[PDB]
Amino acid sequence: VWKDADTTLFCASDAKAHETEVHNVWATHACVPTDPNPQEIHLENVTENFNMWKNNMVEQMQEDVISLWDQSLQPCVKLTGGSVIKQACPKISFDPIPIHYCTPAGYVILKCNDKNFNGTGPCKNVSSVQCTHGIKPVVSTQLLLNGSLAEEEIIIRSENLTNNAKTIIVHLNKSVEINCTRPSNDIRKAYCEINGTKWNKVLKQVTEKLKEHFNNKTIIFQPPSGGDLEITMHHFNCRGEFFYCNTTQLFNNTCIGKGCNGTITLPCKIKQIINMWQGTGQAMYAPPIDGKINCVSNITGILLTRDGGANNTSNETFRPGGGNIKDNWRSELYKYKVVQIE
Amino acid sequence: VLTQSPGTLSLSPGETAIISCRTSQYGSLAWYQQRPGQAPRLVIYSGSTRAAGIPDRFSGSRWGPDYTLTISNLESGDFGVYYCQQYEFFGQGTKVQVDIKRTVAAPSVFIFPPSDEQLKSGTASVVCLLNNFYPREAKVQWKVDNALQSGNSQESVTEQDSKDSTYSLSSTLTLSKADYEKHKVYACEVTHQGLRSPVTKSFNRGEC
Amino acid sequence: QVRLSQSGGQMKKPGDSMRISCRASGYEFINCPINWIRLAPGKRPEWMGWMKPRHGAVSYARQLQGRVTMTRDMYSETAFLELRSLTSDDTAVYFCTRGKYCTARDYYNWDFEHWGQGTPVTVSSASTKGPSVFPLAPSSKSTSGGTAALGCLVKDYFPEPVTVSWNSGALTSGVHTFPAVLQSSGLYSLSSVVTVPSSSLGTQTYICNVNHKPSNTKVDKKVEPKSC
Ligand SMILES: *[C@@H]1O[C@H](CO)[C@@H](O)[C@H](O)[C@H]1NC(C)=O
Ligand SMILES: *[C@@H]1O[C@H](CO)[C@@H](O)[C@H](O)[C@H]1NC(C)=O
Ligand SMILES: *[C@@H]1O[C@H](CO)[C@@H](O)[C@H](O)[C@H]1NC(C)=O
Ligand SMILES: *[C@@H]1O[C@H](CO)[C@@H](O)[C@H](O)[C@H]1NC(C)=O
Ligand SMILES: *[C@@H]1O[C@H](CO)[C@@H](O)[C@H](O)[C@H]1NC(C)=O
Ligand SMILES: *[C@@H]1O[C@H](CO)[C@@H](O)[C@H](O)[C@H]1NC(C)=O
Ligand SMILES: *[C@@H]1O[C@H](CO)[C@@H](O)[C@H](O)[C@H]1NC(C)=O
Ligand SMILES: *[C@@H]1O[C@H](CO)[C@@H](O)[C@H](O)[C@H]1NC(C)=O
Ligand SMILES: *[C@@H]1O[C@H](CO)[C@@H](O)[C@H](O)[C@H]1NC(C)=O
Ligand SMILES: *[C@@H]1O[C@H](CO)[C@@H](O)[C@H](O)[C@H]1NC(C)=O
């Protein structure tokens, strides 16, 4: 017999001690080697309750990613709390690696395997594992990059769909590549390319899932209403540089309800003066490395907030969310919960 | 939907106030109090839980879709306007005001036909006065050629008189001079506890 | 102890924009969202939107979309609200609020335990309009055994307030001046009435004196029984 509990997980990975890359270096000193032959035990006649929105595993991951980022992406100039810190800012090798989170003795991770599980509620197919799957700590906003896909249908996730202050996490069942590039020979200017055919078809599928949750109302997408660039734009880090991409075109309702078929190109910029998601403040980094900077990634999810207001119209409006990077971890850790044996 | 009832409570200190909210969707409901000239104040949250500083004379209940705030033993600082909340939405409010008990008094009903001075403007106002009544609760309905009127009338009520503890009400029906000349019988119907039957005062347009 | 201080009230014309501030203290400003609710008498309290200080994220109420902006200043822990294209319907008292439950890890936005003191804002035209004053004549016959009701209708004026006296203040017994009402035209109207012995109707003279300072208007009007 067991009970829900909270303990200090350890982490495991396949990091290379020879690698100069930042995630690998961190992982070498923080984690242990993965298990070649893991063990999964599918529990029969066992129904367990899961809540991805009160899962403290997310908290521990967040602490680790904040750790990793502080010990790696050190700014040349730190501006926080009315003071100025001037450090050294060498260019780094940056490519996130899968990190496994595991329970110690006395504790076990329960895994939900319901193919349509939405994050909250009971689960029928529960298995018992020692470690989660490998999760890449991909810090991003609006778009969830390089994550895991939903098995069956597109899954809508929210702690409460009626609360316009709760984040909505859209989980895709088919990835859409985003190809972001800063060429060689304004060096801060860049761009991302998306297959408009694939995107508008996934987006069309997403509008149809949201209709199932919102009484067949007209679903409408819109750009963000306000906030810092870190949330009004697709914000992510590629190869060490901080990218800010304009997703206005990505949320084009025209191609959902002709000619839209083609290659979408989002305008991006690499910033050196950014606001730290760590929650501290404003930092100054060095100019971008010379040469073609490129990373191809899977859009595997979307973060959305729903417009509130005492209206009476028969349509809902959604806008690309973000900010709480804890939600990024929720989207991968949702099927896990830690229990203590007796 | 979030429907709050009643609109006004007229109570004496010591009596109890029963305010209700009917909702279309279940979920955490809160109640707020707003004293005159002051910012609102959370009274009950999550349906029945009492906020800090709130005495157990306040209490929340829910039957089906009906959430209820009851306030036993009304004190001076308990009067004001109360609102119900669910997420970003609010009820219309319940005004809880101090009433001085006195014996029941039926209103005197007078009706005033349009001024000949006003009729030269192009509008026609019919005024119906309900004089010196108690309690405050009073219904008025306008009838023109025996047809119930909607949305062309505005009411007004006086503060409780400091001498005789009665109220007075004035309702005004507004029609164009053209619309007005189309009909003969104009009437206001008054129902009040002081009346055995609803009293109707009327006039026939054109005749004196 | 959580405190929410707002900026002073203001008057505005239709078409103007407005900006009010709310300085917060007593708690870690970043961790919880901030709401703006407006209160106007005779209307449901209206949530205008929330704003999360960490990245300035916002959710504006659909019916205000395109007219409202919420920003914040991190250092001075102050939230700001801005409203454009003001109309009479925007005349209200504006509050900033924050929910009761707030931790560094979790919050519930909606149980508003904490309110600012409220910023009243009035939007009205500088235009002023004097009242039409119409007599509310008693009746036909003189009933020597009852009392008569008479008055005057003070109609279509702007803005508040008008005042009514009777016989230059000499007559006060049985007088009732009702609170004014706001008509669809945007203009105000009220009634004043006075009950008097019916036997005095052809002896004593009744004048209602209407004062409307904003239009510099003082009108005397004699209410008398119709002759027919
Ligand atoms: C649980 O597993 C059984 C056995 O494979 C399967 O038939 C069923 O569809 C699963 N339930 C869900 C919700 O995926
Ligand atoms: C998820 O499923 C549970 C129970 O099956 C339900 O109560 C909840 O509303 C669902 N959430 C969403 C976002 O569909
Ligand atoms: C992206 O998706 C493709 C196919 O869905 C997969 O082969 C690849 O491993 C994914 N990349 C990741 C998860 O980084
Ligand atoms: C993904 O889910 C949608 C429904 O939301 C469905 O139409 C589509 O076939 C699915 N794609 C798969 C299973 O590859
Ligand atoms: C990404 O786009 C660049 C041009 O910007 C192109 O040269 C490259 O081949 C693309 N990569 C993929 C994987 O499509
Ligand atoms: C976009 O993807 C479709 C498949 O869904 C493919 O047929 C098409 O060639 C792609 N467009 C471009 C410009 O590569
Ligand atoms: C994003 O691009 C669109 C292109 O029309 C532009 O209107 C919008 O202002 C841009 N957003 C930001 C935050 O720069
Ligand atoms: C949406 O697609 C249509 C069709 O090509 C285009 O005219 C419009 O500018 C697009 N809107 C964007 C990119 O915001
Ligand atoms: C996603 O993964 C690909 C290869 O697995 C990598 O090139 C890319 O940089 C990753 N994207 C992000 C945003 O980390
Ligand atoms: C949604 O919110 C209500 C109260 O507003 C709460 O009782 C309920 O448990 C919430 N749903 C979930 C899945 O947490």
Image (cartoon, coloured by chain):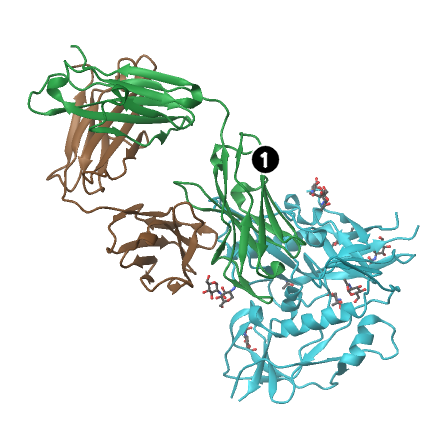
Chain colours: A cyan, B brown, C green
Is residue B179 shown to the viewer in this render? no
Taking depth in this image into account, of A260 and A267 the one nearest to the observer is A267
What x and y, as percent, mark residue B34?
40, 50
The residue lying at 18 percent from left, 15 percent from top is C225
What x and y, as percent, mark residue A154?
60, 62
The residue lying at 75 percent from left, 73 percent from top is A98
Taking depth in this image into account, of B7 and C100 the one nearest to the observer is C100
The residue lying at 15 percent from left, 36 percent from top is B198
Vertical comparison of A273 with A135: above or below: above
Taking depth in this image into account, of A96 and A282 the one nearest to the observer is A282
- Chain on which label 1 sits: C
Taking depth in this image into account, of C141 and A342 the one nearest to the observer is C141
Q: Quadrant of residue C139?
A: top left
What x and y, as percent, mark residue C3?
53, 56
Is residue A300 shown to the viewer in this render? yes
Q: In which quarter of the image is residue B26?
A: bottom left
Vertical comparison of C210 with A138: above or below: above
Give the position of the C terminus of chain C as an image quadrant: top left
Q: Which amino acid does label 1 sit on?
A: Ser
What x and y, as percent, mark residue C154?
32, 22
Judged left or right of residue B208, residue B98 is: right
The number of callouts visible is: 1
Vertical comparison of B39 with C184: above or below: below
Q: Which residue lies furthest to the front in this view?
A: C170
Q: Which residue lies furthest to the top in this view?
A: C228
Judged left or right of residue C180, residue A342 is: right
Query: Under tag 1, what secondary structure?
Result: loop
Judged left or right of residue B173, residue A196 is: right
Residue tagged 1: C17
